[PDB]
Image 1 (cartoon, each protein chain N blue to C red):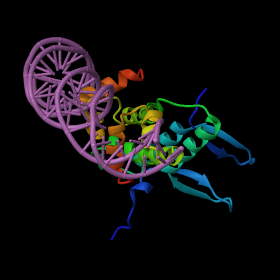
Image 2: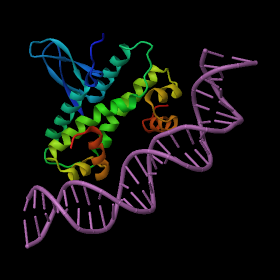
Image 3: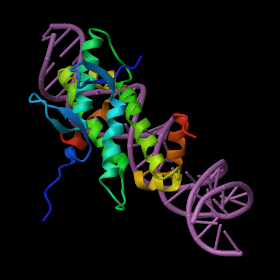
Image 4: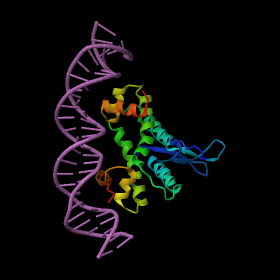
Amino acid sequence: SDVLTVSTVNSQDQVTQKPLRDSVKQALKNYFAQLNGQDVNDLYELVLAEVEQPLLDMVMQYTRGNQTRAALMMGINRGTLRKKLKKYGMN
Amino acid sequence: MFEQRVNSDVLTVSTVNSQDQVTQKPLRDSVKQALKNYFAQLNGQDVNDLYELVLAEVEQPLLDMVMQYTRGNQTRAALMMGINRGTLRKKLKKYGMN
DNA sequence: AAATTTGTTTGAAAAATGAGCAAATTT
DNA sequence: AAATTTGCTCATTTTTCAAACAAATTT
């Protein structure tokens, strides 16, 4: 029912799937705890950065560096794709 | 002084190692495995909307978690994410969060 | 009773789109 | 030699933005 998941082991030594979103939720549950008052200026860019990099890296591994199949696979414009690659300096 | 914390280490998750020890690893790596897994299962089939799929799985808990933190305040939340207050409100309606 | 936030509108700036093309590169 | 992708434009559509400002709610 839910296509993006990650692997998990319990004390009885059994492996089992759970959603990526539960990890994102943990990460952040953790970010906030380890802050006290200190404000946060721009978290939407931060998390986006942390998620766009391993997406781009993984599809360019998969499409063998084919920028055109990549873009089509993601549903974004071929120019958009170049631009984001430039943002992260992987080209 | 203060020890250096790279950005890869600002958002992390609990993992268990080959010596059965508990330990923190980047969210980055959770996102890799998720997709690495997604592909193996895909097996030959095609896609046309992977950006929107990943974007969704990630926007939804980021939004959820931030509103709990500002006890529902949409002005501070949008300020603390650093996005327009009307894009936030737009974005929330998309996921049914109101 | 203040001060702050929500629910709207409006118009301008920035980003994303599709379509074109010659030169380079893979098939 | 032919087919396909790159690198670079243009210009139009869509999304994001800040600045209004009543009316509603929280301090």
